[PDB]
Image: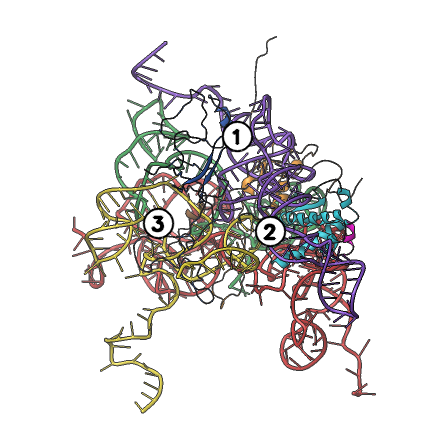
Chain colours: A blue, B orange, C cyan, D brown, E purple, F yellow, G red, H green
RNA sequence: GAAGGUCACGGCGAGACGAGCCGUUUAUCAUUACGAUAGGUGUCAAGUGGAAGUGCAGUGAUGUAUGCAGCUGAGGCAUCCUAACAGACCCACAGACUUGAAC
RNA sequence: UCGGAGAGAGGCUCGGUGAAAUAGACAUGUCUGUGAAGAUGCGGACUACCUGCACCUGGACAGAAAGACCCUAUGAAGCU
RNA sequence: CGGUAGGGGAGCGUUCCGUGUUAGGGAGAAACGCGUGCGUGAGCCGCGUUGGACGAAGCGGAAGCGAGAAUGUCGGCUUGAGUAACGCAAACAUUGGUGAGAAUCCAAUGCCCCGAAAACCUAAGGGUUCCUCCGCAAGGUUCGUCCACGGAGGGUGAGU
RNA sequence: AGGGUGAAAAGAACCCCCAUCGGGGAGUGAAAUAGAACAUGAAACCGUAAGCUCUCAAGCAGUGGGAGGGGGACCAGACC
């Protein structure tokens, strides 16, 4: 809480300690507040174990990802085909008013974006030292933030 | 327009160039010679000897000190072009033109009037 | 960017990389300072220090494979008895880079590589 | 590929000339490096034993 | 002429160019503020693979012992020895009128 | 059939040199309807900060071509 | 007293000529502004600046008599543009020399390609482009102290 | 394709910057805001400086009404 950051630290002295990377807020669920100790653990002491927990990570990035990658379903040759296969398959009309039908599958770009996996049971859970084991999946590559919210199955 | 020195028939252009003088405008004789020597642009020459051309002479020819000098006017104009021909396809879609430049700047003293006044009782 | 990329492939085939590199290498341990792009500097950097650590171990095992890189039988013996022995106390940092004034008529990059 | 109909020329073209703003010395401060009296704008050789010099004392 | 931003530098499981993320040799101030982002190096793992040299058996080829040895790209830990320079600039000085609730 | 990855020449950025088809004029959004009757510029209404880069590329009956199709003009050029 | 094609009825201006070596001008045409006054209109009059020579009031006469479009003609100049391209994919770099500057010149150490070939010789053609000393704006779709570029000299001596 | 600086060129010594290309001064001339691209040198096109308008507003966008702003007025008189 020294290097880089500066203003977020001083703006945290308000009864609390050790600042993370990014402060995240929650909703109503009947819990403790800043009046007893002001410090949440990783036990939740209420969400109950055994149940499934959702994981919202950060998607990766393939740069200016094309359209054949955001759908993966376009035939095309290469050794003799003029479509070179990789081509988006040539979309669009030839003599029709309309309005290029916006929103249709196209190349575009890719980058960091929320994902969320939902469900997924758990095999092991530990507190204090902080550590959790999710049933595979786990959006994004190890190095994001994740919200690891309870479960909004409702 | 006190002293105006430069030249013409330069081998540069009118587009790529000029963008260098538009940064030295309203700048002192120093703030302009400390930036050109860092500009990775070819336009830096003969525009480099330019800022030095407008100066120095105005020091022994007229009554203008080395300081208080600032680029008043500056602009790049297109001179004479040559209609060249380059083959490509049956020779038809061609004209070719070499946008030459002959900028003409000028230096002059600076106005400003400062006169701080305070009271010191003892 | 390639997830976990290292060592630029330049704008020429692989076999074209292990050929030009052989130059900036010997020329570095034969003269001292060599001018080149910032990319090449970062590239040759490792290809040079990795050739110095070999001489530190001596023996012949680090001489047969080494010869596979450089061909000059004059600069080879050097490492096995010249400057590497000087770094016998220093773990790494065999090479040193530094940026300078842009090229002449060309944009960039530009830097001079020399042994510390 | 295709061909433009009416060429406005004026206006439009001019606006697309802002992105090419005067890039004054594209680099950091790298001001006076002490005992340099001037020195180039962009970073340059530091001060210490005669280094980078073709000849020595 | 601060907070902050920006630029540059060293890089990025983030990028066409910009943006965005981490860091800038006290690895920015106190209290340990948890502050090696990269290259190299050392160790380890993994992938090939049991090579060079030498000795021995055989006319030779070839093989055997040391050798499950050596080599070793982006993987992991560790290590900042090299480059991340001391600084600048940009951005300012509690900051409009009327009315209501307070004083 | 679901193709993916990698190595090159372009593409992208910067430095130097440096074209074209085309074009009455521009502050040239969508939609319904209307209109010598499938216009963004009419009318109503909805939507919409100003201005670039890269890419995909339907509209402007886009560009090049007073079409080789038909017909018209007691035209022309060959042939049978 | 709307007006197309058309018919009819009135005028301005431009070049030149007669009436003019009369008169206006170097105390000065032409080119641009302004007074936005004037006529139904195309325009006219006066004048400032710039500029450099003659031009020409009035009526009439004689005109090759004033067009923004005939995919017009000639010349110059915008836009797409500063997008593409910079022309087989036989990569390139470095230490020095010279120069204001050179990755591509020269010199040295190598890589790489070809190897009946992008070697040499010769005919046709081309025709002085060969060599040396200098210079470079233009010609070399980068620069260039480089060049088959330019400007000066030198050089093809067989009865077979 | 491509015309004429001026009467006579006195068509620019020297000095300063640059690579001893180019320019600016010093001078000559009634003039070079006439000098070898040179006379008078408009328009299309391409820029600088100054006043006003200009991000929540759209359609060959001018016109009629019309606030404010930068200047010029008259010893108000409400105008350019």
The percent coordinates of residue A45 (x first, y second) are 41, 29
* Residue H42 relative to residue H18: left or right: left
Q: Nearer the viewer, residue H47 or C56?
A: C56
Mark 1 secondary-structure assignment: loop
Region of the chain picked out in magenta, as a range: C72-78
Q: Nearer the viewer, residue F74 or F35?
A: F35
Which quarter of the image is occupied by the C terminus of chain A? top left
User: Which residue is identified by label 3?
Assistant: A103
Residues at marks 2 and 3 on the same chain: no
Q: Nearer the viewer, residue B69 or C93?
A: C93
For label 1, count other residues whose C-alpha is less than 10 Å away and answer few (under 14), some (14-19) or many (20+). few
Q: Nearer the viewer, mark 1 or mark 3?
A: 1
Q: Is residue A83 above or below residue C92?
A: below
User: Which residue is identified by label 1?
Assistant: A5
Q: Nearer the viewer, residue G38 or B111?
A: B111
Mark 2 belongs to chain: C
Mark 1 belongs to chain: A
Give the mark nearest the N terminus, 1 or 3: 1
Residues at marks 1 and 3 on the same chain: yes
Q: Give the numbered dot on residue C8.
A: 2
The percent coordinates of residue B47 (x first, y second) are 60, 45
Q: Residue at x 55, y 47 (%)?
A: C4
* Residue H59 relative to residue B100: left or right: left
Q: Residue at x 47, y 63 (%)?
A: B93
Per the model, the C-alpha gap separating discs 1 and 3 is 40 Å
Q: Give the numbered dot on residue B80.
A: none
């Amino acid at each position: 809480r020294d290097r880089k950051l500066t203003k977020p630290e001083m703006g945290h002295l308000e009864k609390s300690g050790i600042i993370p990377l990014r402060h995240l807020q929650e909703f109503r669920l009947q819990s403790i507040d800043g009046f007893e100790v002001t410090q949440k653990l990783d036990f939740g002491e209420l969400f109950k174990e055994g149940d499934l927990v959702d994981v919202s990570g950060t998607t990766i990035g393939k740069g200016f990802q094309g359209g054949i990658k955001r759908h993966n379903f376009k035939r095309g040759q290469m050794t003799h085909g003029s479509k070179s296969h990789r081509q988006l398959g040539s979309i669009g009309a030839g003599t029709t008013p309309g309005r290029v039908y916006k929103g249709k599958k196209m190349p575009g770009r890719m980058g960091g974006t929320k994902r969320k996996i939902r469900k997924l049971k758990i095999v092991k859970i530990d507190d204090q030292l902080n550590i959790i084991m999710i049933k595979g999946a786990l959006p994004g590559k190890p190095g994001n933030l994740l919200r690891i919210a309870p479960a909004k199955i409702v | 327009d006190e002293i105006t020195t430069r030249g013409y028939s330069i081998s540069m252009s009118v587009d790529k160039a000029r963008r260098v003088i538009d940064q030295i405008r309203g700048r002192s004789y120093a703030e302009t010679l400390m930036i050109l020597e860092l500009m990775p642009y070819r336009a830096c020459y003969p525009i480099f000897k330019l800022i030095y051309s407008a100066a120095a002479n105005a020091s022994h020819n007229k009554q203008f000190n080395k300081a208080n000098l600032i680029i008043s006017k500056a602009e790049v104009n297109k001179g004479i072009t040559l209609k060249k021909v380059k083959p490509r396809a049956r020779g038809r879609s061609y004209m070719i033109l070499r946008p030459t430049c002959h900028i003409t700047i000028v230096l002059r003293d600076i106005t400003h009037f400062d006169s701080y006044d305070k009271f010191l009782e003892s | 960017m390639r997830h976990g990329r290292k060592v630029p492939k330049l704008n020429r085939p692989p076999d074209q990389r292990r050929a030009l590199l052989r130059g900036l290498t010997t020329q570095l341990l034969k003269h001292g300072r060599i001018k080149t792009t910032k990319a090449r500097a970062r590239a040759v950097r490792k290809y040079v220090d990795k050739m110095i650590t070999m001489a530190k171990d001596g023996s012949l095992h680090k001489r047969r494979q080494a010869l596979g890189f450089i061909y000059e039988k004059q600069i080879v013996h050097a490492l096995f008895a010249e400057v590497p022995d000087r770094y016998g106390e220093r773990n790494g940092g065999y090479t040193r880079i530094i940026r300078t004034l842009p090229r002449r008529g060309d944009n960039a990059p530009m830097a001079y590589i020399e042994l510390v | 590929m295709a061909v433009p109909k009416k060429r406005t020329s004026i206006y439009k073209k001019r606006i697309r000339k802002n992105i090419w703003k005067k890039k004054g010395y594209w680099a950091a401060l790298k001001a006076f490096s002490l005992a340099k009296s001037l020195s180039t704008g962009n970073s340059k050789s530091f001060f210490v034993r005669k280094i980078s010099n073709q000849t020595l004392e």
